[PDB]
Amino acid sequence: EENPSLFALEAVLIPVGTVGLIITLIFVYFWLER
Amino acid sequence: GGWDPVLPSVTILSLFSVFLLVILAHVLWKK
Image 1: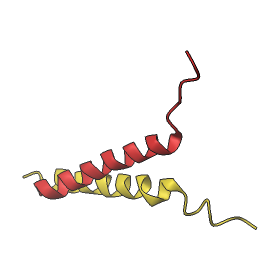
Image 2: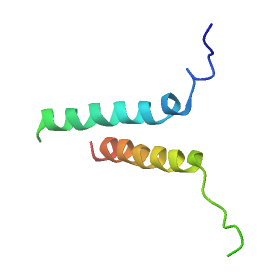
Image 3: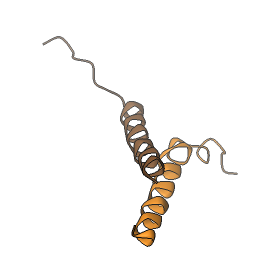
Image 4: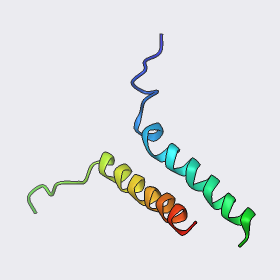
């Protein structure tokens, strides 16, 4: 019933991917400390 | 005065994408 056009929208194509990787990376940095 | 063009939403989203991309590349580069 739904459409796949919205599933492959812009927010999933770049912002969600980058935000998730960026958050994970910064957390990794904090964990390492130095 | 004479109908000034206005930037679209796609361009703004694109800008945010590039900026966040720079953050990812910066953290990996500095790691």
